[PDB]
Each structure stands twice: as C-alpha cells, then as structure tokens.
Image (cartoon, coloured by chain):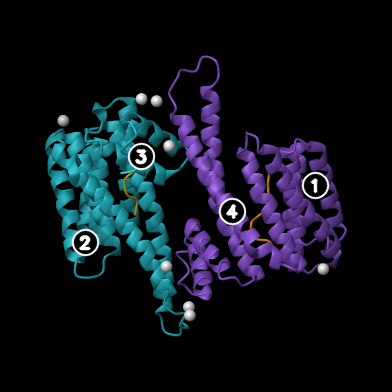
Chain colours: A purple, B cyan, C orange, D yellow
Amino acid sequence: GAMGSMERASLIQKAKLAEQAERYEDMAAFMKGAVEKGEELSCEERNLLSVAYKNVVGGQRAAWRVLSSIEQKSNEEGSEEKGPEVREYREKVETELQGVCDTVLGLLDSHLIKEAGDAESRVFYLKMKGDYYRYLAEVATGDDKKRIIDSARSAYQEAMDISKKEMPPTNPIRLGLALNFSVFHYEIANSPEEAISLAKTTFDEAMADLHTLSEDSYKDSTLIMQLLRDNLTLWT
Amino acid sequence: GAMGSMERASLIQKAKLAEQAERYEDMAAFMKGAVEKGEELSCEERNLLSVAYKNVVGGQRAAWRVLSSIEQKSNEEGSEEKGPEVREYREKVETELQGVCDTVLGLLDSHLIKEAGDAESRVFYLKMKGDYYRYLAEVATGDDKKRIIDSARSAYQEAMDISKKEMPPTNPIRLGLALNFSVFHYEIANSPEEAISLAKTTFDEAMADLHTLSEDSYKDSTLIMQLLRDNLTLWT
Amino acid sequence: AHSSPASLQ
Amino acid sequence: AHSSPASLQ
Ligand SMILES: [Cl-]
Ligand SMILES: [Cl-]
Ligand SMILES: [Mg+2]
Ligand SMILES: [Mg+2]
Ligand code: NA
Ligand code: NA
Ligand code: NA
Ligand code: NA
C-alpha cells in the first residue's frame, strides 16, 4: 500500500488535516493506511474512518442517483435515442462506488471486526458493515441482489443484538444503528412497517433514558433522536 | 490517453453528464480527451472545458488555503512542534494543484491557442492561460515566482489587447478577462491601484454600452459587472 | 430519509 | 475578491 511507509500517528494527523480541508478521498486513503498497520482503532479513529468513507461514497451515491434518473428518463416512451453514453457513465460511477464499498468491507473483514471485543467498537463496525452492504444494495440489480440485502440485514441484526444487551438506549452508536436499520427496512427491504416500528420503539426507549444523561450526552443522543423523528414524519 | 478510444461526441456528452452529477474530475478528463482529438472547440465546448478545470482547481485552491493557514499558525511563537506532517500534506496538495495547472497550460499550448483565430476563442484561451498561471502564482515561493507572475501578466495583456480591438465593452469574455486581470493586479502583482482603475474603467465602459443589448445579453453582461462592483466595494 | 451521521460518540 | 465565472457567453 502507498501508505505503508508512513507512521501510523502521521496518517491519523493527516487524516484530520484532510478533514479540515474537505479532502475526503485523501482522508480515506490515510485512514485505510492506519487500519492496515494492524492495531485496533480508538473511538476517535473509528469515527475518522467512517467520516472519510461516508463522504467519499456519499459523493458517488449522489452522482449515481443523478445518472440513474437521466437513464430512466431516456427509457420512457417518446424519448429520443442518445446511444450508450448514459448507461456507460452510470456504470462507471457504479463500479467506482462498488469498489469503495468493497474496500471498506475488506478492512472490516481483515481484521477490524474479528479483533473488536468491546461493544462500542464491535457494534460500530458491524453497523458499518450493514451500511456498506446497504450502499451496494442501492445499486444492485442482478443475481446477487438478494444476497447483498441479506448480508446487510445479517450485519445489522448482529449489531442490534449486541447493542440491546450491552449499551443503554440513548447510546449514539446504538441510536445510529437503529436509525440505519430502519432506513434499510424502508428503502431496501420493502418493509416500511418494520421501519416505522423500529424507529418508534427506538425513539421511545431513548426518551425514557434521557434523564440519566449529562447535558453533553443529552445533546448527542437527542441529535440522533431528531433524525428518527424526521423519518417518522416523512413515513407516516 | 485513456480517452483515446472514445468518440469526440461521446466525450462531450459525458462531460455534460459529469457536470450534472457534479463529477468535475471526470468532466475534466472527458474534456481533455475531447481537446486531444485535435479539432477546434466550439463556444459551448470551451465553456465546458473551463467549468471542469475551474471546479477541479477550485477544490485544490480551497484545500491549499486551509492547509497553508494551519502551517503558518504552526510557525508562530508559542506554537508546539508537531513534526513535518502539515508541510508534507500542504506540499502534496500543492503538487497536485500544480499538476492540474500544468495540464491546462499544456492543452492551451498544444494546440488550442495557436489554432484560435477568432477573437472570442483566442481571448477566452489567453484569459485561461493567465488564470492558470495566476493559480500557479498563488502558491509560488521560489526562484520561479517572478517568471510565473510575468507569464500570467503577458497572457492577460495579449488577451486585453485583442478584446479592446475586437469585442464590445459589454462582451462577457472581455468583462471576465478584465475582472480577472484586476484580481491579478490586486492579489498577485501588489498593484491595488491598477486593479481598482481597471475595474472602474471596465465597469463604466460597459455601463455606457448596455443600451445596445437585448434583454438576455443585458443579463449576461450585468452579472459580470456586479462582480466588478463587488470587488470595488471590497477594495475601496 | 435521513441516515446516521458518520461520527457517533 | 471575486473572479470570473468559468462559463462566459
Ligand atoms: Cl464512461
Ligand atoms: Cl502527505
Ligand atoms: Mg455497557
Ligand atoms: Mg467583434
Ligand atoms: Na513521528
Ligand atoms: Na450518443
Ligand atoms: Na457515436
Ligand atoms: Na507529527
């Protein structure tokens, strides 16, 4: 790897600089290099890894959606033929997106998840695994679509089982996991009722635990709770 | 070049798709491929080329400014030593910026400018040449700084001479050229009075020619005139 | 729909 | 200071 010669601490320092500069591709390459040093990641480092790749794939997902919409319009009745270019370029963006998802899933499999024993790290990584299979599912169309969806579901479910046993209902990782599993149900698995039920139960159980929290933890938890509420308002 | 096998028309079509998707690196690669087909560019194609590379270098310039500011703070009295990482990463971004500028200047030199005979194309390209030397000047510090600055000045001056002889004072290319030469004077050449004089004369001569214009041309011209006014308000 | 922020405390 | 838009008619 091109980062093999750089110190772990230098990679982390540069990842933070890249974040400040909004250079998320650089940030992701630095954090990939840090992961490949083979040591477990701290909480802050796990968050840097996620921020970097979420922003990279986020740009690709937004582009893919624009191109897919153009492609779908080109396939309506009355639309003039324009040749293979729209499909080709959508496929180019899609392949690059898939490559990023595969890179992240590779890092989680070699060897972040197997070395993660504490609930906060293990749930974070399993959530990430569900998320990047979900992003793969958003563009999947062929024989592997069902297996991609089930890989996302399985990762989220393992994370949910751990989070319910080991974390308080207000924990931001537990909340963000439930939020994203609910989005998976609604947008990927054609299960809007499950999505709504999960969002509601998650929100209500967090509400009843807010009284235990400091001012700062309250702000962290309520920020994610508002996203659950926003989704429920959209879906109901 | 990786675009050598793709039809010119397909490259232009994909450049427009990449613009819609905000995939400006892709857009620039497509337009570079189109330029390398060896045919002159139409007005629309010249604008696609400029949009693509302006957005690419724009992200690099913004990142460079963030990193340069961090680096300068690290060199104040009382600042703790943090090692070579900030300088290294600033240099990485700077080298990538320089590479993009060199690519653009290479396209203009081989062979866009020499084949451009009409004032609208020749002025547009010479303006671009001044602009990308100006971006090089923004990061230049060593023995080549003076020669980079003079290369920007020379390109802008040749463009100005043609635009004053061949274009009306309201022409958007002429206006944008004058705007950017004024920014060159203020920000690069340490000549704020020349910058202010150029912006004022340019604005006043355009104002006196607006009466000749259609509604749509009036809107094009006044949009650039407002930027001259905005700069004068900042500088005076 | 909104998904989670990347950074979670 | 503001510089020119990239696209110029
Ligand atoms: Cl393509
Ligand atoms: Cl670096
Ligand atoms: Mg616990
Ligand atoms: Mg004329
Ligand atoms: Na060190
Ligand atoms: Na076509
Ligand atoms: Na064709
Ligand atoms: Na250091």
**Distance Cα–Cα, label 2 vs label 1:** 59 Å
Instruction: Please name the residue shown 21% across and 61% down the image.
Output: B191
Residue A3's x, y, as percent? 47, 67
**Closest to the observer, B152 or B190:** B152
Q: What residue sits right under mark 1 in the picture? A: A199
Instruction: Please name the residue shown 44% across and 71% down the image.
Output: B70
Q: Looking at the image, is mark 3 or mark 2 earlier in the sequence?
A: 3
Q: Name which residue type carries label 3.
A: Phe
Instruction: Say whether mark 2 and mark 3 are on the same chain.
Output: yes
The chain holding disc 3 is B
Residue A123's x, y, as percent? 74, 60
Q: Is residue A80 left or right of residue B176?
A: right
Q: Name which residue type carries label 1.
A: Ala
Q: Badge 1: how crowded within 10 Å, few (<14), some, or many (20+)?
A: many
Instruction: Say whether mark 3 and mark 1 are on the same chain.
Output: no
Q: What residue sits right under mark 4 in the picture? A: A54
Question: Which numbered tag is attached to residue B189?
Answer: 2
Q: Name which residue type carries label 2.
A: Ala
